[PDB]
Structures are given as C-alpha cells and as structure tokens.
Amino acid sequence: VDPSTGEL
Amino acid sequence: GRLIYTAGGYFRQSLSYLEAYNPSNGSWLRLADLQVPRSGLAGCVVGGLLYAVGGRNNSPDGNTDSSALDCYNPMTNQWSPCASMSVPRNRIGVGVIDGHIYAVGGSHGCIHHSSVERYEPERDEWHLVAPMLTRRIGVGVAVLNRLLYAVGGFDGTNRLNSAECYYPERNEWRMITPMNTIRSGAGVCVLHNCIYAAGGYDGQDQLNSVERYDVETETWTFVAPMRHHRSALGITVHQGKIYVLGGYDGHTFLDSVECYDPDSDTWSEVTRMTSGRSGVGVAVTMEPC
Image 1 (cartoon, rainbow over the protein chains, first blue to last red):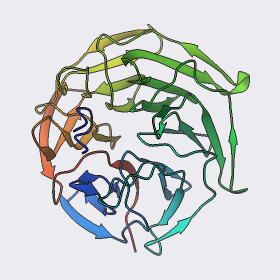
Image 2 (image 1 turned 60 degrees about the vertical axis):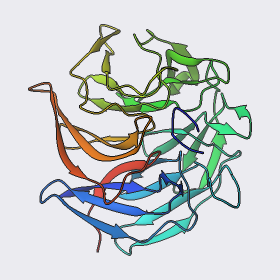
Image 3 (image 1 turned 180 degrees about the vertical axis):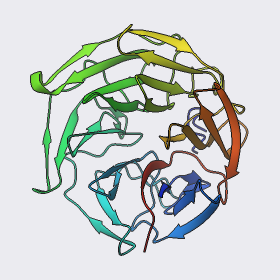
Image 4 (image 1 turned 90 degrees about the horizontal axis):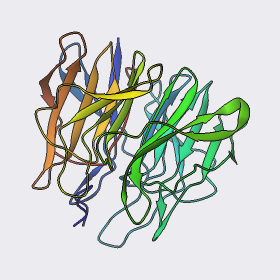
C-alpha cells in the first residue's frame, strides 16, 4: 500500500 | 453559478467518475464518465472547458501511467481526446497561465520526472519547457500572478518540503522558501496572495496541517488545520474558499469535503462525495447542459 495515496 | 468538478480518483481501483458539486444547494451530479479510468491525474479549466491530464490507471489488469489529455465540454457533457504529452505522468501537477496548460513532473514506471510541458489549446500542441530544478511526483502545483509554483513531492529518494517557481518570460526555475513540513501529495492552491499547502504525507503520517506562502514576504505560515488528516487530496478554490475533497488518511479513503474560510480561519465539513476516494483531479467551471 502507498502511504501517500493508499493505492495498492 | 459555477460548480466543483471531480474527475477520476481511486477506491479499490482507478475510477472514471465525473461528479460535480454545487455549493449553492449542496447537491451532486454524475456526468459522462472518463473514457479511461485514472487516478493521480490533475484537472484544470481553460476557456470554460475541463481538462483531465495524466494520472494512471491502477486496475486489476495492471498499472498504466497515462500521457493523455482529455477535454470535457459542459455544453454537451462529452469527453474529447486531445494531443498527448510527450511522456506519461502519474501523480502529476498542473497549472494554467494565459490559457496555457503546464504539466509538471509526475512519474512513469519507476522514474520520477523533472520535465515540464506546455499545452496550446487552439493549436492543440504540447512542447517541453525548462525542467524543474528537482524531480518531483506527488507535487502540488498552483499559479499566482502568472507564475507557476511547484511545491513538495517525492524525488524517488526523499519526500520534499522544498518548492520552486517558474518565470515564463525567462523559461527558468528558481527555488523559493521551503515549507515547514515535508509534504507529498498535498492539495496545493492559490487564494489571494498566498499559495496553500494542505495535508499530504511527510513520510510518517497523513497530514491535517495547512501552511500558506506569501509571495511578497516569501515565508510560510501555518493556518487552522483541517478536521481530517488527508493525503492525495483534491483541492480547489471557489468564491474565496478552499475546498478539499477526499483523500487517504492511512485507514480509509475519505469522502468528507472540508471548506476553508480565510476570514474566520476555520474549516467546516460541507458535504460528502457519493463515495470515498483519493487522487482525483479537481476544477471549477460552469454547470452542465
């Protein structure tokens, strides 16, 4: 998960 | 009466939603979906038309950074493709000057851009301009007094707090005072004489702090923080107010929409998007039909 966007 | 348009975004996968909010009656409207799903894109308005720039289609069938530029006409409620940028730009930054669109930084694959492109509507062409002094993605971009500002972002190694300014007549970039907080994926807009940086990610937690830069005094100052912490948020200005839509707080994709009133330096929850999401392009223009 990307901390900055929440994208997988 | 104008409206706040929100294009694309991300919730479980990149979305192609085009929804609009009317601050006058608090209602929403779903419009023609984007031809291709995308998030990390940037929106902007020129000559009354809405433009969706770059981003990425993060789907189950795979990631695909986009170099596409598409136009949406409120008059017909239809999307038309435009000339594509010389390179794909995910988590892009966008600003407009004299009817010209500037695509700033962004990422392609594992590469972080420092390049910049300028789009000419009438001629329907893109052209590279002087590259930023830094490689930035998740960068916030805003325009004030016909000058373009690139704030925060990620250069591949570190989240940034630095920011710079582009002076058209010289096609040159100059660093400016850095922020007080490392910010990646913050909502960056202009209101009066200041460039605002709201939320974002400092490498540790989604932020709720907001700081503004005074072009004159050349300094940043913290203002009232938003209610919710949020990164990769949509932002825009409307009738002297800052509107932040959605974003990710580290636990859930927000659907809350906060409003900032400089006069009283306070935030308020004004509505909720039909559903939570992050990385949505935002812009203001006339209402449809």
